[PDB]
Image 1: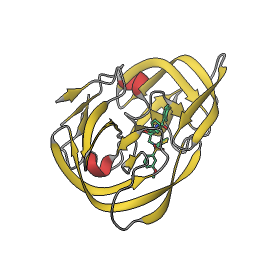
Image 2 (image 1 turned 180 degrees about the vertical axis):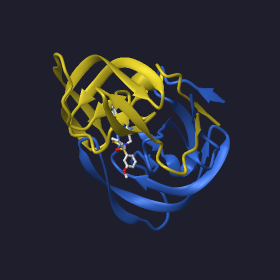
Image 3 (image 1 turned 135 degrees about the vertical axis):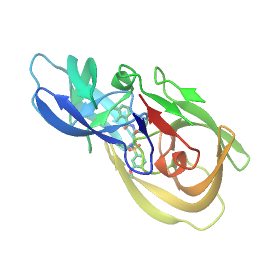
Image 4 (image 1 turned 120 degrees about the vertical axis):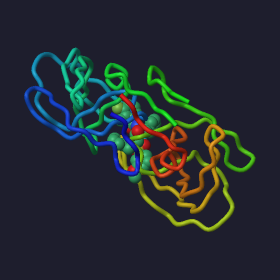
Length: 99
Length: 99
Ligand SMILES: COc1cccc(S(=O)(=O)N(Cc2cccs2)C[C@@H](O)[C@H](Cc2ccccc2)NC(=O)c2cccc(F)c2C)c1
């Protein structure tokens, strides 16, 4: 799809059999979801944004289907204000900016 | 142009006599620039992200040039680590996400 930006670029994602709304965020290096359970081992990590740093849980090699397109990669879980799909997965689904 | 997301989508913008480097950010509703002493009236505001909130100064109707495309809109000025081009200006320069 082509997506314009007069509205937030929110999309439905599928992760672990569950449907969620997430924001396509070219300003995010990483993919960060609100608090949820995912299987397998995680590592504690810290990420920084506009308001400072937070602690997250890092899950590697996680399948997410974003708007029909499959990715498998790193998903961070922690106190983000919103579910965000970052560049690590946007690249896997072939997402570019265009103007 | 077309911009891939292997690295941060940074581009040159112009505001007054300042050429700057800024992030094309589909996840930002608003445009947020690093501290700078713009002329004019402003209103105080709070914006939130990862880590929490920062205080900014909202300036209205500020011409900005983004990769040779002209825009004019609201700009928020405060202690962001990076210059952020938000949806309010990305729409003006014809910017879309495509995959
Ligand atoms: C009114 O609210 C806003 C207006 C403009 C920008 C922002 S923002 O905080 O910068 N933010 C909104 C968010 C959406 C979801 C989580 S945070 C935009 C987001 O793209 C910000 C932009 C940014 C980049 C670098 C340094 C600071 C900030 N990115 C990140 O927070 C970020 C950075 C690195 C990794 C990561 F996972 C994330 C989510 C908020």
